[PDB]
Image (spheres, coloured by chain):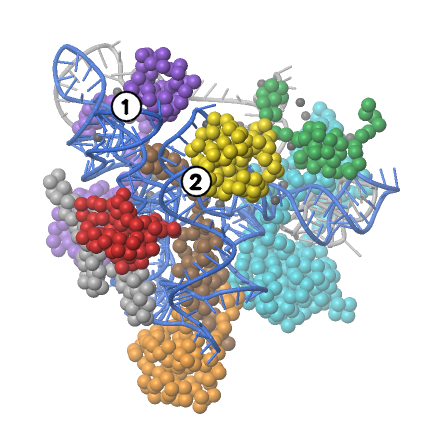
Chain colours: A brown, C orange, D yellow, E cyan, F purple, G green, H red, J blue
Amino acid sequence: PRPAYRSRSLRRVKVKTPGGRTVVHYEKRAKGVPKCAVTGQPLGGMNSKVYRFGISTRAPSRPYGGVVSHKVLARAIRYAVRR
Amino acid sequence: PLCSKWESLITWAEKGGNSYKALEFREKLVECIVYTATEKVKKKKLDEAEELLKYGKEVAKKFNIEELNFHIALLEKEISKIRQRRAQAQ
Amino acid sequence: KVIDVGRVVVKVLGREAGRKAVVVDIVDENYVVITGPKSLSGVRRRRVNINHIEPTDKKIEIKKGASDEEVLKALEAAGLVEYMKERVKPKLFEITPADVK
Amino acid sequence: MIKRFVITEKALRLAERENKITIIVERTATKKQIADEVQRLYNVKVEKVNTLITPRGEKKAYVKLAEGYSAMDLLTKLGVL
Amino acid sequence: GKRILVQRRGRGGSQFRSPSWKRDGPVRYPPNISGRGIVVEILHEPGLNAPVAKIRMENGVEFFNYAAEGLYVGQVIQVGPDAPPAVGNVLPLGKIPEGTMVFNVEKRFGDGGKFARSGGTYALVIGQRPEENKTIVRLPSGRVIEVDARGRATIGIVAGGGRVEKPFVKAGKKYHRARAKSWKYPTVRGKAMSPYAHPHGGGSHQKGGTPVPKTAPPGQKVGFIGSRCTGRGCVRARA
Amino acid sequence: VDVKRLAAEILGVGVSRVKISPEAVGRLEEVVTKDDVRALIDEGLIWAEPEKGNSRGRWRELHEKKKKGRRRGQGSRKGRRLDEEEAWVNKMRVMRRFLNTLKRQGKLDPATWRQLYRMVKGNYFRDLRHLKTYINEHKLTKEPVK
Amino acid sequence: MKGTPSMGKHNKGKTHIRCPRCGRHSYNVTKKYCASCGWGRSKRWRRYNWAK
Amino acid sequence: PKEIFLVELWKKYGEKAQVVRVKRYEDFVKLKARLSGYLYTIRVPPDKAEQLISELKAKNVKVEEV
RNA sequence: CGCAGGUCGCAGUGGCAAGGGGGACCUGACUGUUUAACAAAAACAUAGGUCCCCGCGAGCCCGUAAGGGUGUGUACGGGGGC
RNA sequence: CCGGUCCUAAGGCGGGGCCUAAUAGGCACCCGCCGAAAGGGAAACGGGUUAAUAUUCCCGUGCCGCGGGGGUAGGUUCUGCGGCAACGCAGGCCCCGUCCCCGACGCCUCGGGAUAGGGCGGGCGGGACUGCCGUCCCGCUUAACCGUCGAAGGCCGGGGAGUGCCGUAAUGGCGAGAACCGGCCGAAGGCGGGAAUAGCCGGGGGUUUCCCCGGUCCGCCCGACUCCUGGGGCCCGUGAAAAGG
Ligand SMILES: [Mg+2]
Ligand SMILES: [Mg+2]
Ligand SMILES: [Mg+2]
Ligand SMILES: [Mg+2]
Ligand SMILES: [Mg+2]
Ligand SMILES: [Mg+2]
Ligand SMILES: [Mg+2]
Ligand SMILES: [Mg+2]
Ligand SMILES: [Mg+2]
Ligand SMILES: [Mg+2]
Ligand SMILES: [Mg+2]
Ligand SMILES: [Mg+2]
Ligand SMILES: [Mg+2]
Ligand SMILES: [Mg+2]
Ligand SMILES: [Mg+2]
Ligand SMILES: [Mg+2]
Ligand SMILES: [Mg+2]
Ligand SMILES: [Mg+2]
Ligand SMILES: [Mg+2]
Ligand SMILES: [Mg+2]
Ligand SMILES: [Mg+2]
Ligand SMILES: [Mg+2]
Ligand SMILES: [Mg+2]
Ligand SMILES: [Mg+2]
Ligand SMILES: [Zn+2]
């Protein structure tokens, strides 16, 4: 509780209630978005802010989806097609 | 414009025969226009609000939505009141 | 020219990536029309940017604006029905960031 | 399992206002056991059970009954009132 | 008490131990790597003396090696007897041609590599005795040693050379490096001590000690330990 | 029981501001519950005195004088007031947006825009008036810039 | 500082808690045995002949 | 709570409502269908509001002015 | 942020807040550490320099032993002195 | 639905084994477990109530996990649909495996966007003072949750640029693809719903805390140490793991 709030792991949000008071709500920070397995950059269509685990996310309509980006997928497909 | 994705989804669902999804997409398009216009008017960005309201008028003509016209009329009444106050103060 | 009518290509981007198709029409320098038949490989007939297709060595003989069953008889003449049904499998572990800079 | 009833001012106010009975039970009794014991012994329906352990080492349970039974009436029936 | 610091070091205290949890793993050759591999990462390792390359073999085995200077991400390395002697390739010492600069040399096959593992270091393949399956190599110290010909080495020199030429300008920089290494920092001179704590400690004008024999027991074996000589004359006699 | 604690909790103010009428000194000893305190509050024997807000008439008068330009001389400054870095940011943004608008509308050749842009970055011009005066004097535009 | 000022740091720590076997305030929470009866490190009761 | 804009969509929820609360203003009426899961609110013109309350009472949904 | 004019006092950073300055010698390069409760230093440490034991089944150290630390290390390195 | 409880860290304990005259002594080995009320990590907020508990009680409005029922999209040899694309859209059911990613990370510095808070002019209501003036103070609020929007940044298609062209707070960018045009993904937070029916200010009636009435507004400004985002730099210093998803 109190040392858990003294640590900076949660966001300190000040909010004014309908009762006229000002309170501090301790809210979670967002989880990191999925990254490409080769470049490490965030994947398009999956970089929305998520604050808890267990939320199903819809991958882009492509082979390998939210695993690799379109650049890596296209280049790998070209290499496999030639090879 | 702003809710063109909603327009495309509406026509795509209607072409595919998904009446339920077409109704949901019509609701989403109305939500897009009305929410964005109302936020603009509350922040007093009247030029952007007027552009959004003109687009909503065109969309309501294109899709036969009465609720869009009703909410646009309410927002235009608010815009008129805001502009009247600005003219009186200035 | 490589990207020509009767050429077997593989789509690299989009939903149908890795799927084989047959070029049946030419639009301009940027676009050509492909239909590796949707019952056969899964690529519906539509235009495609030439940058989003990778040409193969294989090529078949058909006329411009050829139909889907025309492409089908050409592929069965070449014996390429199973090659058209096969989907290209990338090797993702080989690629490093230098290849996609 | 039930040791006794709590007939203090807070317990009486809770009985009259919220349809709750306050009991002192064994320290190892769970909410499931308390609810089943209340239902079996008194033939009422238990809405929910809140439990706490007092500073003197006893388990006290606030048993909120369903909306067809009176906590005050049950207390009068048992005569602990 | 009276036990000296070098005697206290052997107990394995936290201030003398190495924090190897800060590193991803040992930099050694796995026993049965063969074929072609891909250089996927070049990483900094706390407490080590060279950048470390992560090699992903064609069959999926991944291992850590010291990066050859000039090695780059996405490079294709060859492992095995059929590998050409190009930079980054892992070859047997028996196959490696004479005069070649190798590193991470294995004294016996399968130990993971022992010699020429610091940044800027290398071993030189001097000769090959195939009838006793041995390879003569010169180590970074200049010492010439025989190694198992079936052992493995990497072609090139270890990257990161010249790291020690730049001075450790502040005590804080050496402090931060020591925190990643195993060194106890800093060190008190022996003659700055009292006699209970060091053989050199003591007198009003404190002095160092003359060399002790090689048979001296622990606690007495400090300073020069069985040295052949000392000073500039010793260096001259060495050269 | 402490009446003032219950009264402060009921009225939502400080106990320092809760005031109990001396006429209810007899009834204070009979106060048992917050309902009793509410009854006394309803009768008006217990009330909350208004809080003090620091009056701002003197500040408003001084702020008008400061806007006119008084009481900001050399003998009234103790530390840094002007922000050099923020001033540079504003100066660059003003000059760059002016020059970029001129080039976008086509009044300035891109080469002349480049020369003016580099001079602005190199601190040739004191202000936008200096930039406009330089442009008009050296005739870098077909029509004068206001 | 070793006297009264250092005595103020003994307000929140602990070396021992009550032992489940012997009930004394002698169970070392870090060493995980009792300093009185030896529970947690010896199944036989700890008692020495030099103690009366 | 959820907000609906189309009367056709809102009627699907309002018809199954345990109660329909009505709040009136000079230009619009808020109709709030209270279900087990959510409270669905729609702002309508007053004439359409009267028509919807008439239809809901015809379907025997409870209506309350709040 | 600036300019012009007028004007009061003994005193205008008017209270609050708020460096005395300079020359020369010894000494330790510097920042840092130290005798909890009489010593803060010119003592210790320090980066830098240099020497020695060591090619690893090493050198040095701990353990009665099983075994252990340096070592997820390898001479641009580990350990030991000044 | 607030914490423990779960996970692993530095590390520790037990059993087997090896050692030991022996153990209650040691631990490299194998196996299991423990190890954080400041790390990782499921889900609740506003109002009211008591003499004493208040995210726990009550009212209202929700969320999570597990399971079930109905409807639906989908399926029922076989495959979901659209877009050149980035990617978008209800995207069938059950079991098992594998891989990847999130979890998951320093310090310094400077640009941008918000919110908490604070102030200014007007309006309404209430209060303070009585030597002169008529000023001064207070209230005018909006939780979680649902929807929609989305700045930087990244990406897609067209375009095909060297007398250059495009820039920043600053470093600067371009045939290894610029200017320019269109599009995709995408924060805090905004707004609507929640919700004025609450709370608050004022004015009355009753009586044991209930009922009634009015207001709860208009236009601007500053703005964080709180929240979000991006750029640049430093390291002989590289800033955890696992559960879980
Ligand atoms: Mg925590
Ligand atoms: Mg965190
Ligand atoms: Mg409890
Ligand atoms: Mg250490
Ligand atoms: Mg001494
Ligand atoms: Mg001696
Ligand atoms: Mg001695
Ligand atoms: Mg001596
Ligand atoms: Mg003054
Ligand atoms: Mg400067
Ligand atoms: Mg002592
Ligand atoms: Mg302790
Ligand atoms: Mg003073
Ligand atoms: Mg000094
Ligand atoms: Mg000092
Ligand atoms: Mg002393
Ligand atoms: Mg002293
Ligand atoms: Mg010294
Ligand atoms: Mg020197
Ligand atoms: Mg000497
Ligand atoms: Mg645990
Ligand atoms: Mg309390
Ligand atoms: Mg005001
Ligand atoms: Mg700047
Ligand atoms: Zn004990």
Examine the image and state in which quarter residue J147 appears.
bottom left
| Quarter containing the N terminus of chain D | top right
Any mark on residue A26, and which? 2
Residue F59: x %, y % from top left: 23, 24
Q: Which residue sits furthest bottom? A: C77
Q: Mark 1 — residue?
A: F53
The chain containing the residue under callout 2 comes to A
Taking the spot 20% from the left edge, 58% from the top edge, the residue there is: B66
Taking the spot 44% from the left edge, 58% from the top edge, the residue there is: A57
Residue J196: x %, y % from top left: 26, 40
Residue E20: x %, y % from top left: 63, 48
The chain containing the residue under callout 1 comes to F
Taking the spot 51% from the left edge, 41% from the top edge, the residue there is: D44
Taking the spot 58% from the left edge, 62% from the top edge, the residue there is: E55
Q: Secondary structure at mark 2?
A: strand
Residue E188 visible to an observer of this rendering: yes
Distance, label 1 to label 2, CA atoms, is 31 Å
Q: Depth check: give the residue in front, E25 or C19.
A: C19
